[PDB]
Amino acid sequence: MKAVLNLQDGVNACIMPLLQIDKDSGNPKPLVNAQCIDEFYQGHSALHIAIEKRSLQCVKLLVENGADVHLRACGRTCFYFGELPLSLAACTKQWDVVTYLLENPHQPASLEATDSLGNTVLHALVMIADNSPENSALVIHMYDGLLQMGARLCPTVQLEEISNHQGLTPLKLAAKEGKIEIFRHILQREFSGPYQPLSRKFTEWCYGPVRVSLYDLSSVDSWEKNSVLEIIAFHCKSPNRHRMVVLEPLNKLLQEKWDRLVSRFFFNFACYLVYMFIFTVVAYHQPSFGESMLLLGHILILLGGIYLLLGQLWYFWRRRLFIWISFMDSYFEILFLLQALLTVLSQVLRFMETEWYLPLLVLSLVLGWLNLLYYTRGFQHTGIYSVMIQKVILRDLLRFLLVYLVFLFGFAVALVSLSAPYRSILDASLELFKFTIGMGELAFQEQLRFRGVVLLLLLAYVLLTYVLLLNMLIALMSETVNHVADNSWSIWKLQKAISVLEMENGYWWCRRKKHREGRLLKVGTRWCFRVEEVNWAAW
Amino acid sequence: LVFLFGFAVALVSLSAPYRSILDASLELFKFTIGMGELAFQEQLRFRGVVLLLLLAYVLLTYVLLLNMLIALMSETVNHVADNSWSIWKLQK
């Protein structure tokens, strides 16, 4: 290794005696496939050094002498290249080296090898990719080159259908990690010519600016498990998961599924409005002819609460297991579960005959209408700007409230201790808050117990609560006036995609079957989806 | 409107507002102009929870108004660049 590890071009002249000095002399164990044991470069060996040095004669000589090509480096900020000499050559843009490594170097390398994680060269190229305009060209060029060469060498195996150790493929791995640049290229691979079979888009006809294409569909949820549509929507922690859903193969597919399931959305909306009206009417007409209807209303409310609780439970601990929270996009499922639990908790007290049921029955009424805003997503385009909520209030408003509560309680305790409350601090605490939203009461105590000393301290609480509000407003404005983007269409489309993917399964009591999109077309010896596209940017 | 009606009917059902819904709706709306009451009375059996409902109502109203103001500011930022004189000329 130290002989190879050099920067001079002439150091290849000293390995010539060493080739046969150790080869034909003892060495029960092999001579050249030695690996480092430093626990950070376990398996680095000597071939990796030769390949990394941008050298071609050294790697030729080592392979000729009998070096092993299937040697993996383990250990190790790390540099992940695929843990294989072929993957290392591919990732470093060495066409001459990679061609020789698998064409005929004696004991040729395999294009379908693993690296103890299930990844192959195609997985490694996707994983190291980037959204930068420079790396994308290299990744696409090498991916296409290796794909073309695989058919030339071994056309009996599909390199792009080899599963990872997590059940993933390069197409799905590019979607989970968020590599949009290599994802879009894979979805729209043309390859017109002798390499037509290894393509995914088959243009049908073109006339003027109009084109008609047939996209291949290995990314449809129906008749598939762990499909690309679920990975891009559920098992994806990336900020660009919304920009990967407006691509041409997916946009029309989601639109034709949303148009099919738009009646059930409003049917559920109506079935929820009727339930809320009945609940409000029953709650208003408290017991403290018409006596028979009250029992029926209570039974209906209990049944509705049980149904909602069962639905939310089946959603949580039976389908979206291993949620891992990530980012709280399920902002309304928790509220639905809370309302469903509170309703049944309030209604179960009839057997207990406890007067404490009245407050809870009120709370379920407050959340119910508050949950009605959930359905404001399919109603026209309403919801494109409704997503301007819960942007930073999850973080900024939390700190604002934490500071405000401390500044409230400290001043309240100070006012109580200094002094017109007598023994209770609740009165002063509520008066301090009423001084903000309402009118309040500003006076010199009760002209007793010294008095007047407490007034000077009150002049600072108002200033603090004013400046905190000003800072919060400034932060909110500075997060909106600048950094403003028209990327709302993508957010609304992602919300509609999630809703469509949820409604496709059906209800927990009547599991509806699946429906496959596209027709079983054939292009040569393949389900396809026809998309028209009009673009007046010709030339 | 739906927020105000839901809170008013909840407060009416809980027994601070009193009697019917229209007067309760007036009491809830009065908080928006600036004047409000938070004494929550003392003869009410279910006190405290009324205070929680009022706090939730005022917080929701404030956040809704802030979001509306932000949307108005964002909209006015866009179409202010070079359309002041032309509209007046078209009206003339």
Image (spheres, grey):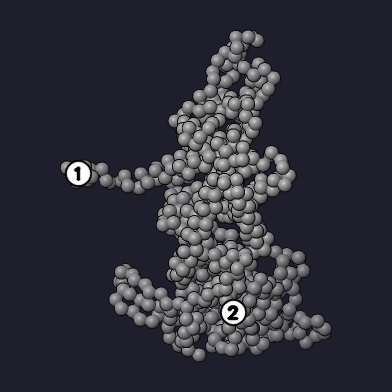
Residue to which mark 1 is pinned: B91
Which residue occupies the extreme left position in the image? B92
Packing grade of label 1 (10 A; few <14, some 14-19, many >=20) is few
Which residue is more in the foreground, A26 or A302?
A302
Which subunit holds the residue at mark 2?
Answer: A
Residue A175 visible at all: no
Please indicate whether residue A434 sits to the left or right of residue A518 in the image: right
Which image quadrant is residue A161 in?
bottom right
Which residue is more in the foreground, A494 or A182?
A494
Rendered location of residue A6, percent (x, y): 65, 70
Which residue occupies the extreme front position in the image? A289
Packing grade of label 2 (10 A; few <14, some 14-19, many >=20) is few
A268 versus A469 height, above or below: below
Q: Which residue is depicted at the point 54% across and 88% down?
A: A152
Residue to which mark 2 is pinned: A161
Numbered disc 1: secondary structure: helix
Disc 1 to disc 2, how far (Cα)? 65 Å
Which subunit holds the residue at mark 1?
Answer: B
Please indicate whether residue A412 sits to the left or right of residue A388 in the image: right
Q: Quadrant of the C terminus of chain A?
A: bottom left
Q: Which residue is depicted at the point 43% across and 42% down?
A: B68
Q: Amino acid at mark 1?
A: Gln
Q: Which residue is depicted at the point 47% across and 59% down?
A: A266
Please indicate whether residue A344 sits to the left or right of residue B79 in the image: right
Q: Which mark is residue A208?
A: none
